[PDB]
Amino acid sequence: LGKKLLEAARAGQDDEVRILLANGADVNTADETGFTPLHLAAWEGHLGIVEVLLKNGADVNANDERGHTPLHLAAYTGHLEIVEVLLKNGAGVNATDVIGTAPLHLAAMWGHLEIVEVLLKNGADVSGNEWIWKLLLDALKYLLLEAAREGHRDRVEKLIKAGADVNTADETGFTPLHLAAWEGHLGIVEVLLKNGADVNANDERGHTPLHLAAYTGHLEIVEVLLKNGAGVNATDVIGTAPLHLAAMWGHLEIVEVLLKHGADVNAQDKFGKTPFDLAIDNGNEDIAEVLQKAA
Image 1 (tube, rainbow, N blue to C red):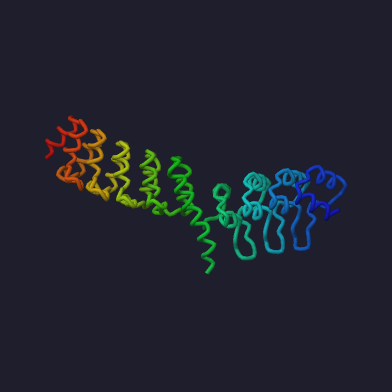
Image 2: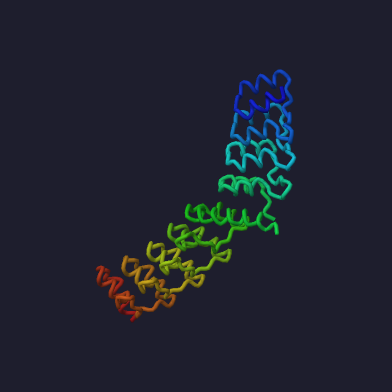
């Protein structure tokens, strides 16, 4: 009966598991190295088996002979709904196995970042074996890049609190601060700068967060970046500075704050064009007037 219960759980045969339990099968039966039906269901992704077993008194924190719990197995195999059900039934979020890894680290092994984040929300402890720490810190990097583009301040704050490196970058050279400025997320710009983000990080085309905020016209982000030391005269690989971008795209208020913070009206891009020239070219007479008076 114990063998039948293990194999019915592995196969996801819910009504067969129900019958076996009703007929007295030990819900915490173990195979020869300590795997219980809940282990195998969690490994295999059979949520229905998981819920039936837990309803019938299964030990949510059963260990096999390597110290793995059902939450370890569900994390490693990427079964998010089972992770949630296990946690809701008292699974130990910080259970550690015989080599020191917890469910968060096994989830990171195959890139199961939503599970990593869920485990963080449920108390996953973030304080040679630094390989374990790298698993966490890399997952946090990827999560922070994702969260910074998305825009939710609470999510980013949580990831930074957990140890995410605010100065990481994606493969194009966009840091979280670039992404937050690009997408117009002022709240995340503020949080990143409060936590040590390089205000003048360059992507591979020489674009700083201030280039991106001037390009997109986000005045409040421009102002916060300038208050934190953004390079008002930084140039991209074609010589374009923030004042050029604000003039090209008709952002009069951004031209004004850039000028207040020391922007150089005489800077020429690689084509010899000053911000005034570009204002003229684009029919932005009001901006051209401001720049000529500041010449």
